[PDB]
Length: 10
Length: 241
Ligand SMILES: C[C@]12CC[C@H]3[C@@H](CCC4=CC(=O)CC[C@@]43C)[C@@H]1CC[C@@H]2O
Image (cartoon, rainbow over all chains, first blue to last red):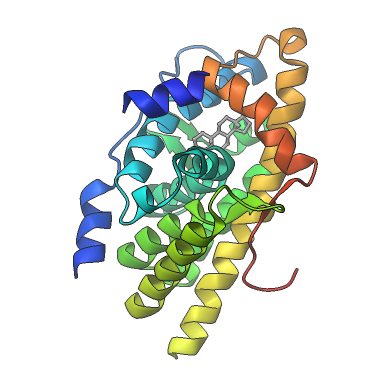
């Protein structure tokens, strides 16, 4: 989930 | 020129690696710093990509996928450009605080890969690549690697890729030039593949060699990069290899 978390955070 | 206005406007600025240049060069230190630089640049690549013309046309899963597949090529291509503009390809300008001379190329254990990257850098000179050509080509690299079995919405991707090819052609003897630039774009992919293999192998043995991988790098290299190395995800070449 680390990439997705970045992606969704902006 | 709306499209080029946007590409110039969204282009990331300077990213430092945080490398301690006072420490003697070592494989572990150089590679740990490269890994941290990748983690930092990833943040910029995501912010840049999400701001690209038409990018939101893609299914959100595909938006995430193309970034996770294409980052190596994107970053190598930009690095080659920085190397060309800053040190006339004399060294690999990974970051202002992480510039590779030949000694570092050797100590990194990536000399062959660095050679290829320096060659790419030199091509920007040999072909007299313009900033506007560079930006359009770099954008196209985001849309140049996909799963063999297709994306979630392949149609929206195909349309987007088509339009970025059209934007490149319009920025572009024209046939000669288009041939040259597509050849240069293709040349990024074998370099990216060699780096994919190298970083994957390094991650697996990272504990044995004191090389640190940050969180996103470790995740992406273990979850997504193997799809490329196993052949499930492949580059799109212009010319047959
Ligand atoms: C993947 C890697 C860390 C990230 C590096 C990569 C070499 C290419 C590169 C160029 C950049 O400008 C950002 C960092 C990256 C993307 C390195 C090769 C081995 C190392 O593990």
